[PDB]
Image (cartoon, coloured by chain):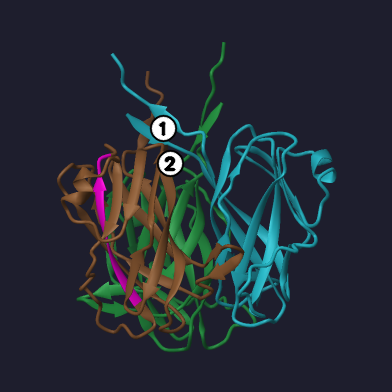
Chain colours: A cyan, B brown, C green
Amino acid sequence: SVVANYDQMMRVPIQRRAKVMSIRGERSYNTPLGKVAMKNGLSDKDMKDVSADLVISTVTAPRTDPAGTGAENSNMTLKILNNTGVDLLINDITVRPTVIAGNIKGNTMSNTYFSSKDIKSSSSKITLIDVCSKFEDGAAFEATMNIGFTSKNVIDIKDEI
Amino acid sequence: SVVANYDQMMRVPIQRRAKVMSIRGERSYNTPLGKVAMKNGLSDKDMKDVSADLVISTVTAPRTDPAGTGAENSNMTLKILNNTGVDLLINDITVRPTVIAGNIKGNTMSNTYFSSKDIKSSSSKITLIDVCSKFEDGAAFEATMNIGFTSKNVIDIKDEI
Amino acid sequence: SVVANYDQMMRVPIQRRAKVMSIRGERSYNTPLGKVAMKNGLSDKDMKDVSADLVISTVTAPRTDPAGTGAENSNMTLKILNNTGVDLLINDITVRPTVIAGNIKGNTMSNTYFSSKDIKSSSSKITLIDVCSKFEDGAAFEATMNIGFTSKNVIDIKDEI
């Protein structure tokens, strides 16, 4: 009996402003589990109108902020609408520098926390994922948030008789 | 000809105390490759009695300590009993902050080394994996050790004639 | 309908010298997608002679250097010849400490940027991947560059009638 599953990494362009990290700009592309779209601060109604199988957005006001955080930290609350027809789980998140116009941005160390919640493949449920990252100081900067997605719909092949 | 394999990320709750990192508490849950159980400092006999397909524990006294380490470093020796019936390999380890009771813990930068050993799916062999991490200072703290597991039992599908 | 893909992590032994990171020594082994070989500064002709399905090398003079980098940064330009017959994409890169002869090396924090380019499974095309990492200071050191590879040849199984 053998097992296999699906994994997918997505680069989310972000901006850090003091305590808040947000998605900058808007991205729309296709992938094995369908069309993906991302854009900051969308409503639980707008997300539903977006023409895509997976829409990632955020809570404009990520109010939620862990106790013990300092000026070097920053938060974000991801909003996910999954209509891919596959259960999704985030297995990893990393904030990395970016290179734009031959210029390095987000040239800083980083570590990140993120809640583990199954991202149900429903059509009316918006799943929220809290993300809290630590950086070198409190300066603003642009960077990329790499989100590793894994599917829970595991393939199991057996050799029966 | 196409190939596919299985990957799985597990969050191990840990505690850092000077030079030693240990698993705090005990976790037991089910996953595609079976029931998983984890608990600090178990004997090579106790692990064998544990009712689970994959038991992760540690060497209470992780004696082994790389030369060149300072007060900011910490070690751990993972003990793994794999009865999942699948060859396993750790492809990644990261120490991240945790959020407990709305409180951030392990709010520190981190980098980790870990040995690459195939984790044989035997029933009497306990595989050991050395882990050495670097942190900002020598202060104690709680955090999460994210271990990425990959299977070596790769699925290969060909279209023969 | 379920989906599954293939992922593979490779440890590349590296050396950091000021602004340049290079592969130290030479590695040759077999893996699900074929034999892999790696060695620093190979020509676009030598790589082609190497007896392997996947050859990773570098641009001896990684000239390309992002603006905004300091003494703590370092660059590398990976050269990849993919003859595995599978489209490859790098989903992750991390620089970690190494342990040699019971000695920790590269005991430093780190963050890395890397371009996202599909690595076509052609036979005459050498794909280049820019990598820029940030470290604690400008000191030289040895370490390991963990490159996570994912395949684009996704397996899709449906239950038709």
Vertical placement of C40 versus B3: above or below?
below
Q: Amino acid at mark 2?
A: Gly
Whether residue C39 is visible, yes or no, is no
Q: Residue at x 24, y 76 (%)?
A: B65
Residue B107 x %, y %: 54, 74
Residue B26 x %, y %: 37, 54
Q: Residue at x 63, y 61 (%)?
A: A131
Q: Which numbered marker is on residue C85?
A: 2
Q: CA distance from mark 1 to mark 2?
A: 8 Å
**Local secondary structure at mark 2:** loop
Label 2: chain letter: C
Q: Which residues are magenta?
A: B74-83
| Magenta span includes B81 | yes
Q: Label 1 belongs to which residue? A: B1
Residue C81 x %, y %: 43, 55
Whether residue C27 is visible, yes or no, is yes
Vertical placement of C113 versus B6: above or below?
below
Contact? badges 1 and 2 (CB < 8 Å): yes
Vertical placement of B40 versus A126: above or below?
below
Instruction: Describe residue B79's horizontal placement relative to residue C111 as left or right.
Output: left
Query: Main structural element of the magenta stretch: helix, strand or loop?
Result: strand
Label 1: chain letter: B
Quarter of the image for the C terminus of chain B: give it.
top left
Residue A138 x %, y %: 68, 81
Q: Residue at x 84, y 45 (%)?
A: A46
